[PDB]
Amino acid sequence: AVLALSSDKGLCGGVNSFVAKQARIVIKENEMAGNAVQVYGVGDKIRSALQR
Amino acid sequence: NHGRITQVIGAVVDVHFDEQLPPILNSLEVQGHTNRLVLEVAQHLGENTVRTIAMDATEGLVRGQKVVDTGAPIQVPVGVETLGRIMNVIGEPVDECGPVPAKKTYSIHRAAPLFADQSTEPGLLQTGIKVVDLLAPYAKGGKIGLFGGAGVGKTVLIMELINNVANKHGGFSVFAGVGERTREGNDLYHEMMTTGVIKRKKLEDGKFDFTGSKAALVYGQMNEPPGARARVALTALSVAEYFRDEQGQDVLLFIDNIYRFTQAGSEVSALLGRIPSAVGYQPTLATDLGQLQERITTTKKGSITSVQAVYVPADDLTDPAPATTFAHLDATTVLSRQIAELGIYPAVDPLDSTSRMLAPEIVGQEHYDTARATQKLLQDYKSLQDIIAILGMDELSEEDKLVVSRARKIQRFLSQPFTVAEVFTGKPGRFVELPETIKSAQTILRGECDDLPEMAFYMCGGLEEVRSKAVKMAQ
Ligand SMILES: Nc1ncnc2c1ncn2[C@@H]1O[C@H](COP(=O)(O)OP(=O)(O)O)[C@@H](O)[C@H]1O
């Protein structure tokens, strides 16, 4: 279970960008070995970043 | 008929005949003068007075000098003897190789072909350039325009098109220079004598044999008056009409800085007594251009492909001259300084560029859809320029970031090192076929090249070079 903390407003630089980058890295690393991943999040920015 | 000079104002000459007047467009020779000064009639004014434009400088003329009417307009020789040879507006060769031993002469001024004697058949050209082969396909037997300011690569693009078309053409060709640098004129002459487009052989007794040439040359350059600059394109058009009317052949016609054809009028009408239009241009700015362009047309006898370079003063594309010229073209290519400052060459703006031979009934459906998808991508990237400049890419969503990435990648992929640029770029030239361009664009749009960097697409041609460059840059 990956808990990604983020914000709800924009103009925050690229902090949510780096967060979602690390989260993508972790997910793609842990889904190869076969570990079933779940995603919890805080803020709409991570949702918009990882939806598609 | 004999006449007398009464008044001289720069490039304009007022003449007085006693018995009988000459009609308009007729040629007159000035007698009490060092060189062969020729005057072309333009107007009638009364009192048996005539207004004329001089094909050379008026320094030395006198009110009282004598003038002789030739009875016909200016006459330029025609035949296979003009091939492999330079010729000024009055037909006199300036190659310093002898005279032009041609049987027949044609008038500089001819009426255009009629409506019924036209043939609009859709063909394509193999330029070897990605941007035009993909997004602005050139029409075999049609007009093509290269619009640009100063220092964007019009002359370089024309030299590349010459290298990639005329050598691989077989038929004939013509090059007109209307206010271009004599340096590049000599350079073209020597590159043609190198590549065999011009085949000069020095017979004994100082004679010459240009047999084997496939390109004529007409040069009225910046060191010439307006009257000697506004009548060169007509000479070249006569030379090409001889080919595509009598010989029946398909010809090419490269023209450099057609804008001067208007500029001359703009620095002549004021002396001819005409009221200026918006920006000092003429009231005849549209008819004087259409009477030139309507002679350029494919017909049932032959074909003229045409490649015109159009200056854009002060980088303003809303000027009346280019505005009018846009309506007369079958294919277009607008170069930009904003894109040249990024080091992208050819600096073609693929959104201002357009064509009529892009429809799915001419080029295929995969070509059509790839071109339209590229245009959509570049417009979607244009629409984010403001918010990127103010805030930055971090504000954007992920779809928009992917769009920006692919748009920068396809911008850098739509750049090509030419062969004629090797002298000041060093890197060798890259001819690029169309199916290769289309596969590469398809892959870049799909997403099969997002893993690569952005500077791996710069000056690489196809994708194998891009991938090799990304490999070498990984180190
Ligand atoms: N293929 C090219 N690659 C890189 N730079 C180029 C290329 N072609 C032109 N440039 C630049 O374009 C400029 C001249 O272009 P040119 O069309 O001759 O000027 P103009 O439009 O005034 O006639 C030069 O600075 C030249 O270095």
Image (cartoon, coloured by chain):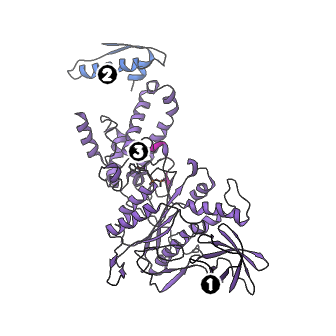
The disc placed on residue A24 is 2
Q: Which chain is purple?
A: B
Whole-percent x, y for residue A21 in the image? 34, 21
Camera-side residue of B120 and B334: B334
SS at mark 2? helix
Q: Indicate yes or no: mark 1 CB to ligand 1 under 8 Å.
A: no
Q: Residue at x 43, y 48 (%)?
A: B371
Q: Which residue is mark 1?
A: B70
Please tell me if label 2 and label 1 are on a single chain.
Answer: no
In the picture, which quadrant includes the N terminus of chain B?
Answer: bottom right
Do labels 1 and 3 touch, CB within 8 Å? Answer: no
Of helix, strand and loop, which mostly describes the magenta segment?
Answer: loop
Counting residues from the start of the chain, the first of labels 1 and 3 encountered is: 1
Residues rendered magenta in the picture = B338-357
Q: Nearer the viewer, residue B156 or B249?
A: B156
- Element marked by disc 1: loop
Q: Amino acid at mark 2?
A: Arg
Label 2 vs label 3, nearer the camera: 3
Q: Identify the residue position indicated by label 3 in the image.
A: B344
Please tell me if label 2 and label 3 are on a single chain.
no
Callout 3 secondary element:
loop
Chain on which label 2 sits: A
As shown in the figure, which amino acid type bears the numbered disc 3?
A: Ile
Judging by colour alone, the chain drawn in blue in this rendered image is A
Q: Is residue B285 visible?
A: no
